[PDB]
Image 1: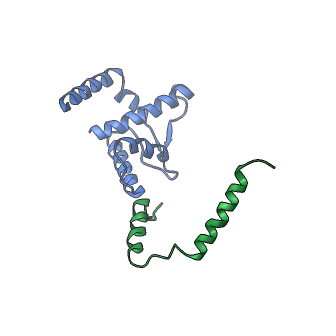
Image 2: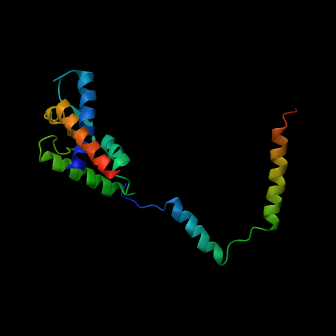
Image 3: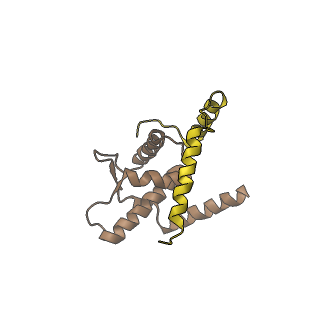
Length: 50
Length: 109
């Protein structure tokens, strides 16, 4: 349509180099809290017992 | 040229569809440029640039206008398929073309 874009094959590559030096921290308080709560939520939604 | 004859075959397919739908000689057969880009995209390959493949398709159509099979694209990006195509690719000629293409494929093996 007259405009360039970045295919996925470049999305991944740029995700690579810019995670070499100073990638954002994952092991954190917030990530553990979020997975805590998500594990809480998903479990309560599967077993259909009312 | 072979790549031109491929587009000729595609045009002839569209023409037979239109002809068998509306009958023979009823008004004029028309096709939109949109429908022709995908068809070639199967064979000629995809260069990942709509501009370049559009230029390729327009160049092919222009080279076919030199043979009198199609008009040039008009305002709505549509092209009339001149009825002369019905004679350029008919049973006998298609049979000869198929034989030659099979011979080429056999050589390739």
